[PDB]
Structure formats: C-alpha cells, structure tokens
Image: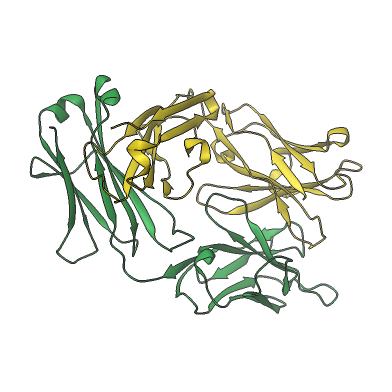
Chain colours: A green, B yellow
Amino acid sequence: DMVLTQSPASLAVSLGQRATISCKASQSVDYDGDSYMNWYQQKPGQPPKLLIYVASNLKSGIPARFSGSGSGTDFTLNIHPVEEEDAATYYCQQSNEDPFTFGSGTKLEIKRADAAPTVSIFPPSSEQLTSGGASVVCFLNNFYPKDINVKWKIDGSERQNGVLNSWTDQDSKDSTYSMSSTLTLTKDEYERHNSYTCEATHKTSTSPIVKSFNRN
Amino acid sequence: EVQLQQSGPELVKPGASVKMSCKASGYTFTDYYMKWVKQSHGKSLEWIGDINPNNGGTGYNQKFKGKATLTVDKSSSTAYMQLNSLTSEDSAVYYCANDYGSTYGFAYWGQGTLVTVSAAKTTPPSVYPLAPGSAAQTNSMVTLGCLVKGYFPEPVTVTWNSGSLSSGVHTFPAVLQSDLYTLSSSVTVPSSPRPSETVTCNVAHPASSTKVDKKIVP
C-alpha cells in the first residue's frame, strides 16, 4: 500500500494570508504525464468535498482561491486568500493504484481577534428534578482562542467532579469557538445548597467572567 | 443534480451483520462505478471497494475482502454494502460515492451512515428545556437551551422550531457519561422573540423512533 504523508498536521493562519498544505506520496503517482492526486475539504459533520483533482485541476464551482501543484511524489495545496469558510480538515488522495489512499489530514484554524465568551447559566428544569436529577448547564458562546477554563462553584466552594464539557468546532462565519459545561448532581445534593456559579478564565489572566443564580 | 441518498443509522450486535443502501439519482446509474469509503471517529478515510452497476463488477481493498460485500440493483438505481461478522472496529461512518464527471477521484458523496456495533440496548434521550428564569428582557439578546441527556446510541437530531431558527444555534458534540450519551443545544434570540413568539426544540433519536418537541417557557 502507498502511504500519503500530509504536513503540517495543524496550522493557524490569519484571514487574507496564505495557507500551504503539503502531501508526500511514498511512491510516484504519475501515469502518462498526469499526476493523480486529489484534494478534499471536510467541514465537521459532512462528507468530504472534492476540491482539486489530478494534481492541479480546480473542480467546477470551487473558488479560485484554491490551487494545487506538484507532481511525482510531492504535492501542495494553496489557499489564497484565506477566508472564514476555510476552517476545515484537508486531505490529499492518490488515485494512481490499488488501493486508493487518503492523507493523514491537516486541520486549518483561522486566527482572529481575542473575543470574550457569552456566558449563560441554567438551573435544572422542574421536569428533571422530579426524577431525582439536577443538571446545571453553562453555555460559553463565541470566544477565542479555544483555550478557556470553566470553574464551577457551589455555595462559594469549587466543585471538581460531575462536570461535562463539550467544545464546538471553529465557526464558519466568525471563526469563533463555543463550549458547553454541565455540572451534574443529584436532586438531594442540589437541594442542599443555594448559590451555583459558573466562571470562565482565558488561559492565565486573572479577571474572570462569572454568572450565577440562587435556588430562589 | 447527482444525488446519493444513504440509509439511516444502525446499531448492530457484535458478531452479527448489517446491510446499508445508497440510492442514486440525477444520472445514468450504470454509467458510473459506485465506490464505498469508511471513516472512523478520530476521522480518517479508507477506501472499501467499488462496484460496476452494469455487470456487478467488483473491486475490493484487500483489508475489506470478505468483510464487505458490495451489491447493486439496476431497477432501483440502488447500491448495497453488507458488512459481515461485525466487531467494534466496524463502528464508523460509511459513505458511498461516485465519479460522475470523471475527475478520477470521488466527486459526489452520500451523507453517510453511522454504524455502531454494540451489545448494548438502545436508550431514548431525556429532553429537558433550559429557560433563563426571570432574567433580562429589553432589546437585549436572550439565550435558550435544550438538554438532551442519557441516550444511546448516536446520533440525535436537535432542531429549533422545526428549522425556522438556524441562526444563533449551537449544537454541541455528544459526550459519553457512563455508557450513555449527552449533548445540548442552545439558541440565541432577540428579547422580542421570546417569551412572545413560541420557541420549541425538536429532538429526534432515530435508533428508537423517539421524537420530542419540548417548548421553552419561563
């Protein structure tokens, strides 16, 4: 089997800049003067999208910002200028021989201006409590960079376990991330405390963003 | 427009087998080869094999010879793939594609089929609405949430207002608490909308034909 090594693995690039992804086939993928290497774009949640086929052909409908090059065993995909809708994982795939092979992929992240998350905390729904469960949910929307912390405080003290965080992939419209944290306790543990705080921190800093509520 | 419609998700017991379909339209079914790719959680694509709709010709990636079994049905322009003796490794997403336009690659793809190989029983989700609870309400945006917790297996489709609301939505990826799944979605709307105009969240869990419409009230 032929090995397709993509490089780099991850790459951050500011809007308008240039993005260059490499692909190195272990063998040659030329055949009668044509290099059979294709490139796909894949945004989280959907099937890959054919961008460029046979090394340098831009599929009809693809923005001219994209452009492939290379031959033999070394190929390159070029994006200029980079846009918000480009944050995705990219793949080169050889069609030269059995079995068809895909590259190890390259995630493309967009750099932008630091942005504060929009925290919103939610107490447990009556429905949920009735069944002996209490899930406090905290939404930290549209922040940047992806590196953020979330500390949960119950009656002043920090709650360690019972937390479940889930990040969103970088937005296609504004290049921001979002995260959801859920502190899950039992109706008993919940009913025996009053103040529930959810606070976010950006890497180091010191000035957090808090949100809280009282059981009344 | 060439169109490839793949079957719904599947939860299969390990050791068993499963068959998925891929309905083609918008083109001469026999003219083009039908190809199959598998992609796994951590994301990484693998070619399974191709099939010649015309004569039932078949091409298999050595790894999948014996595991996959491509088949086709001319009269219905439908492609089939059968996976035998499933094991947890076979838990992934399978796409069917074709080279309409002869780009010598994979030009068109289906939307995928998620197969979960597991001895576990399917558990429906518990849909809980998330309301602010006596908060802001004066020309200032308001965030609402819907918590979908304790379900199995993946996936679940959350929607806001049958789909009228697409902007402001943020559906987070499911996490695995215990041996169950939990995800949540949020939607930001102008103070005008709610509580005035109705805001519902519609959760659907295919594996169990579970359809819920929880209304977000204050």
Q: What quarter of the picture does the C terminus of chain A occupy?
A: top left
Find residue A49 and report its horizontal and vertical position in percent: 65, 58
Single out the residue that lies furthest toward the left: A156
Q: Is residue B209 visible?
A: yes
Find residue B24 and report its horizontal and vertical position in percent: 78, 42
Q: How many marks?
A: 0
Q: Is residue B179 visible?
A: no
Find residue A66 and report its horizontal and vertical position in percent: 63, 73
Whether residue B36 sits left or right of residue A130 in the image: it is right
- Comparing B198 with A105, the one in front is B198
Single out the residue that lies furthest toward the right: B55
Residue A146 in the image: above or below residue B155? below
Q: Residue at x 63, y 55 (%)?
A: A48
- Comparing A186 with A71, the one in front is A186
Whether residue A120 sits left or right of residue B200 in the image: it is left
Residue A96 in the image: above or below residue A154? below
Single out the residue that lies furthest toward the top: A130
Q: Residue at x 39, y 71 (%)?
A: A112
Quarter occupied by residue A14: bottom left
Q: What quarter of the picture does the N terminus of chain A occupy?
A: bottom right
Find residue B9 and report its horizontal and vertical position in percent: 59, 33
Residue A208 in the image: above or below residue B215? below
Whether residue A185 sits left or right of residue B189 in the image: it is left
- Comparing B45 with B75, the one in front is B75
Q: Residue at x 39, y 61 (%)?
A: A176
Quarter occupied by residue B112: top right
